[PDB]
Amino acid sequence: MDVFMKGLSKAKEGVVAAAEKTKQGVAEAAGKTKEGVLYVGSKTKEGVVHGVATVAEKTKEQVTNVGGAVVTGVTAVAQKTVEGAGSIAAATGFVKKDQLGKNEEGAPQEGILEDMPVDPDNEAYEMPSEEGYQDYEPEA
């Protein structure tokens, strides 16, 4: 599924590039405007600061509520996905390969293989890596 991983990354890259482009365009327009300077906000700045402190306390309480909602979504999504996965496997009938009909076999043959068997097993007890080994002597 290397193609799926590549496609997933491609979409992520597009989203990042789009978000960055929009942010840059907005920042430029926000500073390009000279109306804000003429309008003046120094008086509102002090008012905004007091308002922000009040909002901050209100925001903190709301933030906690939002955090809980976010957790619920994560809990609800993970659980339903686990259940849906099981349902899919059940419908599939847990099959390694999808095939129809029976595999006909016949025409017996005999012969030998020039290439000896790989034999993954080393037929050796071998020592455990837990004991380890010494790379230095006590002398020095």
Image (cartoon, rainbow, N blue to C red):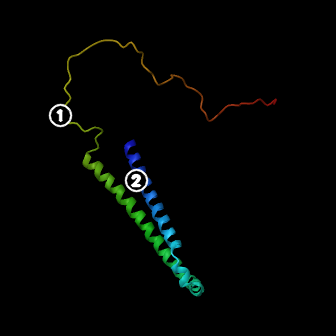
Contact? badges 2 and 1 (CB < 8 Å)? no
Q: Quadrant of the C terminus?
A: top right
Q: Which residue is more in the foreground, 48 or 100? A: 48
The answer to whether residue 74 of the structure is visible from this angle is yes
Q: Mark 1: which secondary structure? A: loop
Instruction: Work out whether mark 2 precedes mark 1 in sequence or the reverse, and give the earlier one.
Output: 2
Mark 2 residue type: Ala
Q: Quadrant of residue 37?
A: bottom right
Q: Is residue 132 left or right of residue 17?
A: right
Q: x%, y% of residue 95?
A: 28, 41
The answer to whether residue 1 of the structure is visible from this angle is no
Residue at 62% in and 36% down: 130
Q: Which residue is more in the foreground, 76 or 52? A: 52
Q: Quadrant of the N terminus?
A: top left
Q: Which mark is residue 58?
A: none
With respect to residue 81, does 140 lie above or below?
above
Q: Quadrant of residue 116?
A: top left
Residue at 38% in and 60% down: 79
Q: Is residue 73 left or right of residue 59?
A: left
With respect to residue 73, does 136 lie above or below?
above
Q: Which residue is more in the foreground, 56 or 124? A: 56
Say which of marks 2 and 1 sits in front: 2
Q: Which residue is mark 2?
A: 11
With respect to residue 110, does 123 lie above or below?
below
Mark 1 residue type: Gly
Q: x%, y% of residue 16?
A: 46, 57
Q: Is residue 37 left or right of residue 68?
A: right
- Mark 1 neighbour class, 10 Å CA radius: few under 14, some 14 to 19, many 20 or more: few
Q: Which residue is more in the foreground, 14 or 139? A: 14
Q: Mark 2: which secondary structure? A: helix
Q: Which mark is residue 101?
A: 1
Residue at 52% in and 72% down: 32
